[PDB]
Length: 355
Ligand SMILES: CC(C)CCC[C@@H](C)[C@H]1CC[C@H]2[C@@H]3CC=C4C[C@@H](O)CC[C@]4(C)[C@H]3CC[C@]12C
Ligand SMILES: CC(C)CCC[C@@H](C)[C@H]1CC[C@H]2[C@@H]3CC=C4C[C@@H](O)CC[C@]4(C)[C@H]3CC[C@]12C
Ligand SMILES: CN(C)C(=O)N[C@H]1CC[C@H](CCN2CCN(c3cccc(Cl)c3Cl)CC2)CC1
Ligand SMILES: [Mg+2]
Image (cartoon, rainbow, N blue to C red):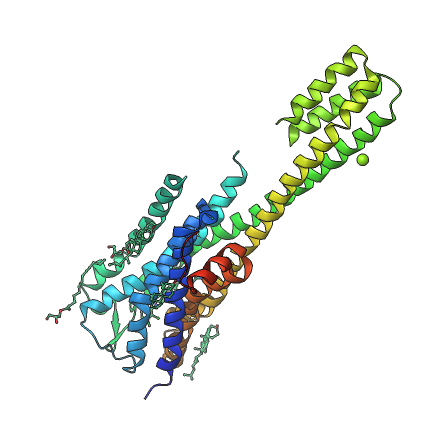
């Protein structure tokens, strides 16, 4: 008689339906066809595959008191799917953080589907000791007729190698991305005063000194931020001949090109900080929900002697569902914090699929 299967059946269908909707939204709606959204589909494939393959077998074992109810050579395989799909999500979340960072030092699907194939192959490579050695020796994958990783080298080596190369690189490249977008906003409303200051200088002017210097100083300050470089140069010639009343009126026709360009760049940055913050929640929820399973699984190995493994085991059976639930919640994040995903999901529920 088990309570727990009534709970766990919820988490599986949330996982399956939501991650299908994310897969559906990137496949269909054109305003999601960018490289960072191509990763989020691949992530959702992993979360949906976790929900189809790994999670109902976990529920099944809950209904046999953890005494493993299937063929023995499926235990080593099930473990490989359970580790792969998670190792897939951590190298996904690392890649997005890293790819958006290299995007800031810069001015395609084949961009993305090489990088996704690069990440999946580093997951398939890293998880591959499990069935190659587990299918040889049933005592890497079974303890006491319960299917679970029973090799501590695979846990210790896998956890740090598979989760601390990527987490480190993800938490550095997330932090540096925040600092790159803070310097860009700082550097742009620096150029605001420099251009704006100099406008008030050219409108006050007496002579061709105050106009030619203050368009020289406008031009280099324009060069830090395309088309307005010519429009300063189209007005830099008027002051050089001495046409001062003409260059002053040409500059209030620069004021409109300036206000138009600054706001567009400024909207783009405020977008990309809202977008950096959405991932940061996808990133934050992943660690925090796996955090109790992770720490306890490592302490299983560290205090084999000094601790009640019945209690340690009774928590791992509980803590692994906290991290399963993480599959369910990536889609909810998008629903409340993207207009684009919410509008799309709200039309797939109305069975209406034409952009
Ligand atoms: C371990 C194996 C047997 C599990 C099964 C993996 C299956 C479900 C995976 C692997 C390859 C995946 C497909 C690869 C690429 C695409 C194209 C994309 O535009 C829509 C989804 C779609 C069609 C994927 C759907 C899910 C998929 C079919
Ligand atoms: C009763 C006698 C034999 C002693 C048993 C001590 C056991 C039950 C103790 C010692 C080590 C402990 C674990 C150490 C680390 C963590 C991770 C953290 O998120 C809190 C829970 C958890 C998982 C603890 C639960 C209780 C624990 C398993
Ligand atoms: C950022 N942080 C800290 C992390 O990502 N931590 C990680 C914690 C471990 C997660 C691995 C996923 N599997 C491992 C194997 N598990 C298992 C399988 C069969 C039987 C039994 Cl009993 C068990 Cl317990 C279930 C979960 C990935 C994330
Ligand atoms: Mg000033």
